[PDB]
Image (tube, rainbow, N blue to C red):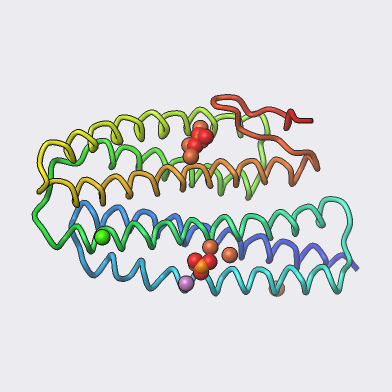
Length: 225
Ligand SMILES: O=[P-]([O-])[O-]
Ligand SMILES: O=[P-]([O-])[O-]
Ligand SMILES: [Ca+2]
Ligand SMILES: [Fe+3]
Ligand SMILES: [Fe+3]
Ligand SMILES: [Fe+3]
Ligand SMILES: [Fe+3]
Ligand SMILES: [Fe+3]
Ligand SMILES: [Fe+3]
Ligand SMILES: [Fe+3]
Ligand code: NI
C-alpha cells in the first residue's frame, strides 16, 4: 500500500551512493595531482563513464517510481529532487574527469612549484561535498546555511591562486603551460564547490517545496522578481 516508501528510499539511497562515488572521484583526481599518479588519473577518466551510467539508472528509476506510484507531496519532492541531484553529480564527475586530464598533461614536464592553495581548495570542497550529501540524506535547513560560508573560502582561494598563477605565466614562457593547467584545475574545483552548494539548495527545496539560494555567506529564500 505504501511500499511506495520502500521504492522511494531505495531511489534516494541510489542517488546517495552515486554521490559517495563522486566524492571518492574528486578525492582521487586531486590525489593523482599531488602524487603524480598516472594510473589514478586514468581511473578517474574511466569512472566518469560509470557516472554517466549512474545518471541514466537514476533517471530510469525515477520514471518507474513516478509512473507506478504517481506520488504527491514529500515522496514526489524527493524523487524530483533526486533527478536534479543526479545531474549535479554527473557534472561533478565531468569536472573530476577534466582535472584528471590536466594531471596527465602536467605529468609531461617537471613540477612547477609547491602545491598549497590548490590542496586547500580541494579539502574545503570535499568537506562541502560530504556535507551536501548528508543534507540530501537528511535535510537540516538551519545548518544547510553553512555550505554558503564554506564556498566563500573556496572563492577567496581561487582568486589568490588565479593571481599567483598569472604571475608565474608572466615570469617565464617555460612556466606558462603548467601554470595554465594548474589554474584550470583550480577553476574546476571552484565549480565543483558551486555544485555542492547547489546540492544543498536542491535538498532544502526537497523539504520546503520553495527555492532557497546561497547569496555569498547567506542561504536566503530565492529573492527575485
Ligand atoms: O557525459 P557528458 O554529459 O559529460
Ligand atoms: O561563489 P560563486 O558565485 O562562484
Ligand atoms: Ca593542454
Ligand atoms: Fe527492496
Ligand atoms: Fe547529464
Ligand atoms: Fe554533464
Ligand atoms: Fe559525463
Ligand atoms: Fe560563493
Ligand atoms: Fe563559480
Ligand atoms: Fe564559488
Ligand atoms: Ni562520458
